RNA sequence: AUAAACCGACGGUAUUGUUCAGAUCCUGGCUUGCCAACAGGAGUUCCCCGCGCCAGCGGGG
């Protein structure tokens, strides 16, 4: 049995990116690999130019994300999408200089009434220990948020720690149970995969490599 | 420090003018509130005081 660090990602608004080079900023259904690394990298004091420990975090940690349905008054509330018409005045026209446009337009998608429970474990050749990752989520250095800085948390990042055989068995200890799980480690009775391009290329800033979740449906 | 960061969707604007709800219409007939009754019992009133026969009588609060 390995040690797991259990996290809770809850808030009225979330955003988990999909590939884009456009003014449209799309969200997926559950947290990304890159987004979870960034969240951890925020709790730790990692700066954007520190590629060394940026790569040390990525090589040390793997995730498992469970989608949690909001239950209210014994009624189920579904996750909905939200489109924000987001404008910027005096936005940069070039990457150097002070010339700017009057108005630019962007379109940003959010999730509403979404909540997630994240299982976290160490790779066989990890650098850090779950003990110091626990410290980081309890006392973050940079401000933690759900995808975008405008999206605060309504529940503490830290949920618990535990020991278990597989990520599914670990997430079982924490209500609410029943949601679909996406894991970096495969579990025995499941064979479905979820393709994604959310593996941050750390040697190539703001670029992403293809990878795959192992899909584990809830009962 | 997360397709992240930095980041307004903005600015102007009467809903206006006209218009009876109106005519007709008993709530109405019947019906004891009635039988019994001393307002008498019971001297606690806590003081100061003055004069006694010691029983009890007075003036001040």
Image: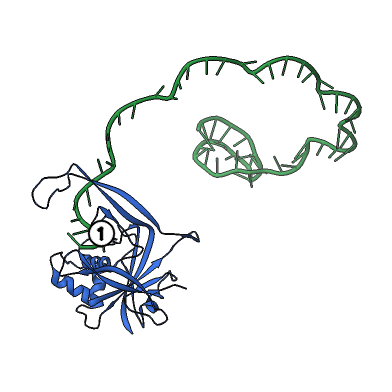
Question: Residue A130 appears in which quarter of the rendering?
Answer: bottom left
Question: Residue placed farthest to the bottom in the image?
Answer: A1
Q: How crowded is mark 1: few (under 14 residues within 10 Å), some or many (20 or more)?
A: few
Question: Residue A172 appears in which quarter of the rendering?
Answer: bottom left
Report the quarter where the N terminus of chain A lies.
Answer: bottom left
Colour applied to chain A: blue
Left or right, B39 with reference to A215: right
Which residue appears at 32% of the width and 78% of the height? A185
Q: Nearer the viewer, residue B56 or A160?
A: A160
Q: Residue A5: x and y, percent?
A: 31, 74
Which residue appears at 40% of the width and 82% of the height? A188
Q: Residue A210: x and y, percent?
A: 26, 70
Q: What element carries label 1?
A: loop
Which residue appears at 35% of the width and 65% of the height? A30
Name above or below for residue A148 compared with residue A56. Answer: above
Q: Which of B27 and A56 is in front in this view?
A: A56
Q: Nearer the viewer, residue A184 or A146?
A: A184
Q: Residue B21: x and y, percent?
A: 64, 18
Name above or below for residue A12 compared with residue A65. Answer: above
Q: Residue B51: x and y, percent?
A: 56, 36
Question: Residue A70 appears in which quarter of the rendering?
Answer: bottom left
Q: Which chain carries label 1?
A: A
Q: Name the residue under label 1.
A: A20
Q: Which chain is green?
A: B
Q: How many labels does the image show?
A: 1
Give the color scheme: rainbow, by chain, secondary structure or one colour. by chain
Q: Nearer the viewer, residue A129 or A24?
A: A24
Left or right, A162 with reference to B25: left
């Amino acid at each position: 049995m390995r040690s797991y660090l259990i996290l809770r990602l809850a808030g009225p608004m979330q955003a988990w990116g999909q590939p884009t080079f456009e003014g449209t900023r799309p969200t997926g259904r559950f947290p990304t690999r890159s987004g979870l690394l960034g969240l951890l990298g925020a709790c730790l004091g990692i700066q954007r130019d520190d590629t060394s420990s940026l790569q040390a975090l990525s090589e040390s940690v793997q995730f498992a994300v469970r989608c949690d349905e909001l239950i209210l008054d014994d009624r189920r509330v579904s996750v909905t999408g939200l489109r924000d018409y987001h404008t910027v005045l005096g936005a940069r026209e070039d990457y150097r200089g002070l010339k700017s446009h009057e108005t630019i337009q962007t379109w940003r998608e959010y999730l509403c009434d979404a909540s997630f429970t994240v299982a976290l474990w160490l790779t066989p050749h990890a650098t850090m220990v779950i003990s110091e990752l626990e410290k980081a989520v309890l006392k973050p250095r940079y401000t933690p948020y759900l995808g975008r800085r405008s999206c605060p948390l309504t529940h503490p990042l830290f949920l618990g720690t535990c020991q278990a055989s597989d990520p599914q068995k670990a997430l079982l200890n924490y209500e609410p149970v029943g949601g679909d799980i996406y894991s970096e480690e495969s579990v025995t009775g499941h064979h479905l995969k979820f393709t994604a391009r959310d593996e941050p290329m750390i040697t190539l800033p703001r670029q992403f490599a293809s990878r795959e979740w192992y899909v584990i449906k809830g009962g």
